[PDB]
Image (cartoon, rainbow, N blue to C red; front, side, top):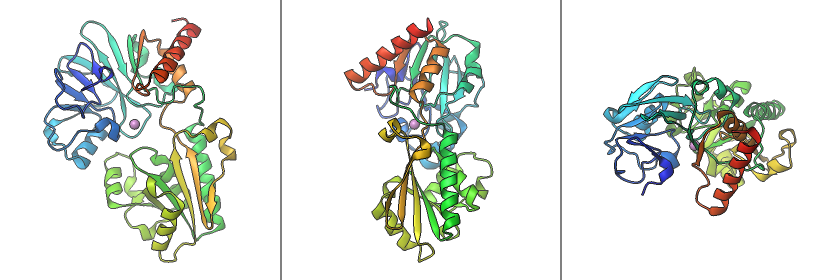
Amino acid sequence: TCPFYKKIPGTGFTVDAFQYGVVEGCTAYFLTHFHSDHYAGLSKHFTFPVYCSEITGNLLKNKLHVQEQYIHPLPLDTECIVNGVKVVLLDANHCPGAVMILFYLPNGTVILHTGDFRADPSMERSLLADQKVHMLYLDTTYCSPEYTFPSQQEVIRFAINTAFEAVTLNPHALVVCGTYSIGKEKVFLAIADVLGSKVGMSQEKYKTLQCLNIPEINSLITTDMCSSLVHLLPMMQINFKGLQSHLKKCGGKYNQILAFRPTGWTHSNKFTRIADVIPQTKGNISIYGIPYSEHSSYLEMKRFVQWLKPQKIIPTVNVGTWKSRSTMEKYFREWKLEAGY
Ligand code: NI
């Protein structure tokens, strides 16, 4: 049964609630983004209206075969009426097509559902600037002060400089980047751009990327692995056994692999700067774990919430344990006492 934190009171609406069968009283199902824990349950047999971004709707039609007549894509930054209720979709700074949803309830309550997001000061000048928010349904993935990581720009600078140096020293080195979902495309695209190569990948992953409205994509990716020196593999294959096997398949074109695993946070973050990151090496294979996050750090989250000043916070992540829930509630109270709302 659908948990309360997926339900929007005073409406017929749910958010990211496709794995519970027919939810009683739901007239419209919203989908914030195309990640499996959020879309779980959708397929070509779904017959209720799904509301989402254009990019999410391209993925639903092409990857899950949801029929067109049930997909209702909305433009961003635009007031729309859904089943009698004003809504707006805002960029979430998460993966491609990911949105936050503003609901303007018929009684005057305003609700922000962040979906998954990486808070940014640029959000302080969106349509959120223009009215009060009563209730915040918050992505609390990294809601504890241990969770620090660098900017996405510092991480991509590290990656590009590392790859360019390795391949210039050895023109017979292959670069490999792990993936298992959409998101984090800048990692492999930025490295291929500095090397003058396309990114090579499987037909299934090329199909996914073709749904994303990324400019000039036909110029940047390919299914012809032999023409590319940046390859994309499943995240599960980014280990010494998996990479040794891949190197066999390339027929002596290459004699070294440099591989990247774009994790979120790992506790090497509590001690080490990005500048100081080193790989795990075995023979002619090196693997870098890089802290490229598409979720808020603790400090980014705290700044957003202290700016927004919501009357009530509903966490959407880490809700399954009493210790996690009590930790998050203590931080919310600190934030509110420090800022004065
Ligand atoms: Ni996500």
